[PDB]
Structures are given as structure tokens and as C-alpha cells.
Image (cartoon, rainbow over the protein chains, first blue to last red):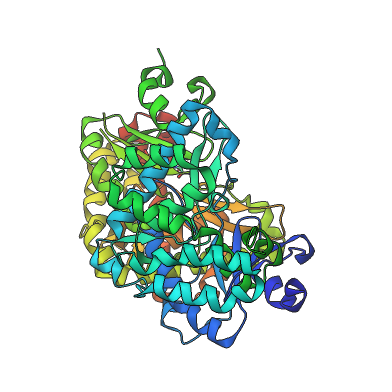
Length: 285
Length: 280
Ligand SMILES: Nc1nc2c(ncn2[C@@H]2O[C@H](COP(=O)(O)OP(=O)(O)OP(=O)(O)O)[C@@H](O)[C@H]2O)c(=O)[nH]1
């Protein structure tokens, strides 16, 4: 296992912690070891090791944004960002748990939850208009054109003909999408990455995790994720409160949202997560 | 009425559905702080503290950006009575009795080094230097306050000793190379425990933060944990030159006078008595 293989390193980083009682989340590039108060990104390849300096810079930049919540703070020293390669990266662990959709059936909760989503997305939107932020995060072009190519290459082989025709209609609108690079975009903002303390009182946003796919891009990508997980009414409430309920934005959201399962499937494919891949491919095979 | 009742409107906004009478309120030199599970709300008492709260929020923003190897209180929300919501760093202080175990002591010393390195490094960053106070000849203004306010409370001997201590303090070089927490006692350093050896969670109470001499934070560590443990920290960090030992000792021996001067102004006669122990 990953915990077994990196036993010696983990014992230095987490002294006196039994690596039996640790969790592991799979990434495309990093295996992230989850401890009580912190997470250890272990590179899967030397190429992955070479990306961790940049990642440390990215997470530092995110930790200084005004999002109204926490983010995984890098626990390396600043000079780590100057390295060719890192053998690991330690980040603070954001406390709290995800929110089941059930909770949003209460009207006051939904109001409160939507409001804090808005704060977060407004923070991200404004941060993506900052030249120092834009300079530190990736901003790939024709990502939608390219993403469609990656689905056809990497996911169609796992699909039925029916699933492939379904995917094709969904990929069809992508080539028409405007290529927007205006906001900081988490890129995988499903419910499991948005952590709440519902200890005392109504749900209060603790923070946001799993920034692997972060970029300067289109805010509709993150609103789509929320739409996918929580449905139309809750989305609409976020759009109203944030002032993003225009037809142009809504159109983009709907187009991206229709691809969101495929986004999760492509991710699960690349990071070897089999149950996430099965879920994402639900109705495609 | 109560502080919680008094601020109940704001608390219902900031902490929706949270029973205000279930919260706690700690105090300080400038701020009333309401403690909730995962965050605190800073309220100013003085009209001056209300005006300075924007600056402190911008400072905490900068601190939340640095690489210190641990958490700091992240600004979540500011508004106008002005308020500032900060994250609650989890964990508790480490009892000095923990340092009796030498494997614990090594790990703690190591983590302190990382913190102080981060603080040191940050001092060089001009962005940080701009957003943080860099008061020149701070130690001399202090000495004048001591003479003005404390000498009259003191014996002739006390004044001899104190004057000797302020003399040493004037001869110190005016150093502004590092971010200096300013108040780095055991209470403001929080740890994760009962999951292997103590891991540094984060640091709080940055109100006295400045660009200055790192010997100030190192003295504070030594005050709280003793000179054996500080020596461990000084060796790991490569700070065990005698110039540094001098600045630390000079600064260390002003803590009684600092406490007394604080207690004098605070009208906190218990502290003033303890601070002046030996000076009267
Ligand atoms: N866990 C946690 N506790 C905090 C935090 N901020 C304040 N506290 C607690 O609330 C108290 C309030 O005191 P300070 O934060 O020092 O108050 P202050 O008046 O702003 O500070 P000074 O001007 O330096 O005296 C602290 O001593 C802690 O007990 C925080 O971010 N996390």
C-alpha cells in the first residue's frame, strides 16, 4: 500500500503516528495522505515531484485570498517554491464535513448556505481579475475543445454505444462555449470538497479542499458543479444572490453542467479511483 | 446586559442559529473577542481600537499568506461598531512538563525553529515590511516610560538595577530584519496532541506584531520554557552565537519591567506587584 511504501517518510513527518490509522485520497499526480490536522502530498512520479514547488506557490496564493473560509495552507518553507522537485508537500487540513442535499430542504438553511457559497465565488471571481493571482495560476486555452478530445480518447473505450451517443451530444455544445478566463476556478467544487461546521446552529462554511484542478477560467465551471450536486432551485438562489442569473451565464452553466459527470469520470480514470469512475460512468455503460 | 446580549444582532448575522449565551468572551489590551467553535469575532472597546481594526485585518491577511509551517488566524469577514472575524486556530498550549521527554523536546524545538525561520525570512519580503509596523528605537521610548512611571514606585536599589538594565538595552543594535510576533509566550502557541508527538497547530495573538529583532521572540520562548529548551532551539536553528545570547539576555531581563509597566497602565495591581518583585 501507499502507506506501507512511504512508512519511513510518514514517520518523520507525523512522528509517533501509526500509519495504519491514516486515510489516502488518490490524485492524478499526488497520493494525498490524510492525517488528523494535515495532509501529505506524495508524488506518484518524478514529473509529479517536479510540480510540487509550483503547487506550494499556488496554495500560498489561495491562503491569502479573501474567500470568507479556510483553504489548505502549505506547511513547507517559502524557499520550497524554488526547488526543482519536492519529495512531499504538507498542507493544513480544513476541518468540517460535507453537506447532504437533504439539509437544503429547510429554507433558512438554503438561504444561509447559498449566501456563503456566494462569498466564496465572489472572492474567487475578484481574485481572478488580479494580475498577481492570474500570473501564479495556470490558464489553459481551448480547455473545452481539449476536454472533449480527452473524454473521447480515455472514456469512450469504457462506455457502451448508447453512452457514447449520450456523451457526444453533451460534448457537442462545448466547441461553441466562449473561452472565459476571468475567475479563479476550483475546477472540482462538488459537495465533498466544501466543508461545513454544523456544530452550533445553521451550516457555517469551514473551508474548501482538493484544489488539484485550480485555474484561471470560467466561473460557470464551479456554478455547474453546484448545479450538478444540488439541483436547479439551489443553483438559481446562488445566481440571484451573487448577481449571476443572466442568460449568458446560465447557458454556459447548463452546457458545462451536462459534462460534469464526465469530468468526474475522466478524473477517476486518471487517478485510478475505481468507485468514483463507476459512479461517474453511471448511465454511460 | 452582557457583551453577548449587547452584540446579539451582529452575532445572529455572523453565527446564524448560534445561541449567544453559549459563547465565551475573552478580553485583551484593545479587543473583546467572542469565541465560537471554529472562529472568533474581534470587537474594539476603545474608539482608537475601532479605527485601527482595518489595519489589523490587512496585517492578519498578510500573516495568513506567509509560510510559517503552521496556521494563523485567517480573516473571514470584516465590517462596520467595526468587527473582524478570524479563524480559530485549534489546539492548546504545551505544558513545560512535556519537555521532560527529550523526543518531545526535539520535535517541539524543531517546529519552533521552522516558525522562527519563517518569521525571519518574511522580514526580508518588502511586501511584509510595508504592511507591518517598524518602530525605530522602540526600546528607548520604553526606558523613558519605565523611568517616568515605574521609578517612583521603586526603591533606590531597584532604580539602580533597573537603570543598569535600561543601559544595556540602549546599547543594543536597532535590528529590523525579521517579523517579530512580540508576544510569543507558551499560551499563544497551540499544539495537536494525543496523535503521536505534539504537532504545532498555529500561533495567535499577533496584535503586537512588528518588524524587529528576533531575539525578542527567542527571549519569550526562554521565559516560558527555561534556558535548557531555548538552548536546544538556538542550536538547531544555528542562533547560538554570543551576540544573540547577549541581545536575548538584555531583552529577557526587561520582562519584569514590561509586565510592571503594562500592569501600571492597566491598573492591574497583582501583575504590577509581581513585576516589581525585586525592584522594591
Ligand atoms: N483558538 C483561538 N483563540 C483565539 C484566537 N484569537 C483570540 N483567541 C483567544 O481569545 C483571546 C483574546 O486575546 P487577544 O486575541 O490577545 O486580544 P487582543 O486584545 O486583540 O490582543 P492584545 O492587544 O495583544 O492584548 C486570546 O488570548 C485567546 O484565548 C484565535 O485566532 N484562535
